[PDB]
Length: 188
Image 1 (cartoon, rainbow, N blue to C red):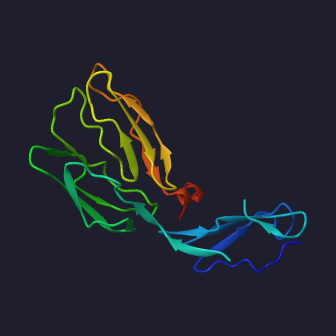
Image 2 (tube, helix red, strand yellow):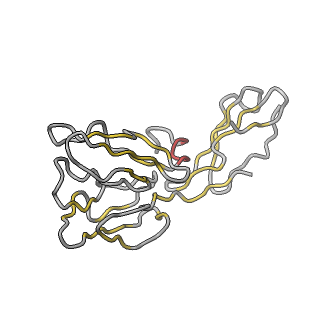
Image 3 (cartoon, rainbow, N blue to C red):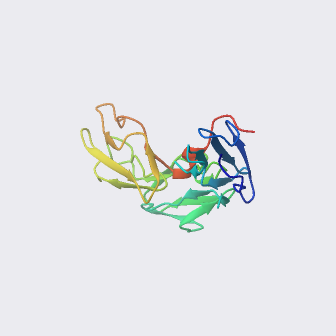
């Protein structure tokens, strides 16, 4: 039987099959916090295995770069509820959201801010917050590549091609906190 010394600071947990081997423990934290660790599995040995628990603040990813413009405030990551504001230098027009708020799930609201000089066959595809991009030409057939920085998790296209219609192929890559992958759907 697995031991009961498994309380989480600031949060709660559920057991799938009580304290028995095979039982999955799932931690939950209040909105805007995440459990570290997120779960434990009760082993046949009678000891827990993660695939002292604490609830830690969610943060949204900071820009790694923001070209031909400035953002404020300038931080290495952002608190839940915090806003970041974007402004472009002369000769560039801001596309996307000039003000964005960090949501409790670690994602920014609105859409990626981009300072675009309007010179490409395709628009400047921008650089989503936490991503690093390769490529500087936005003509028909040109390609950009992306990765997510640090331990951030990528969704969407890591390579995009500027198509004949002036649309980048695929979908904009987005970088998420790795602990967001412990969040369920449909939570109160």
